[PDB]
Image (cartoon, one colour):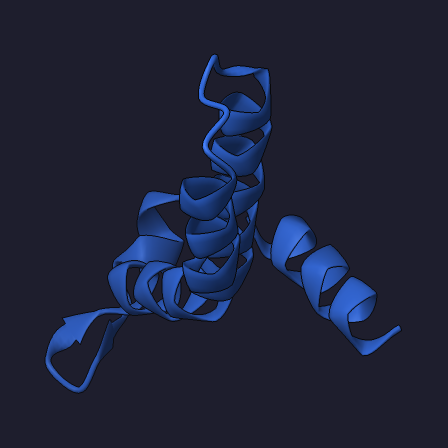
Amino acid sequence: TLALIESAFFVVILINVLKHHTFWGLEVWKWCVLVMVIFSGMLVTNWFMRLIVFLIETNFLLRRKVLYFVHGLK
């Protein structure tokens, strides 16, 4: 799907001469890294949320209301 293609592209995306290039008065490598981080922020947040949900499931907490609120506000 569209999400899978974006995730694969981000994974694929993730040399002194190459980094020496300057764009708009800034390092080309730094700009590319920032762009990749911005693009993959959604995937990183989704992975973190999944990990948190998995940890909570294995946790000793058993409050249905608290669990429901956490699921809603995740």
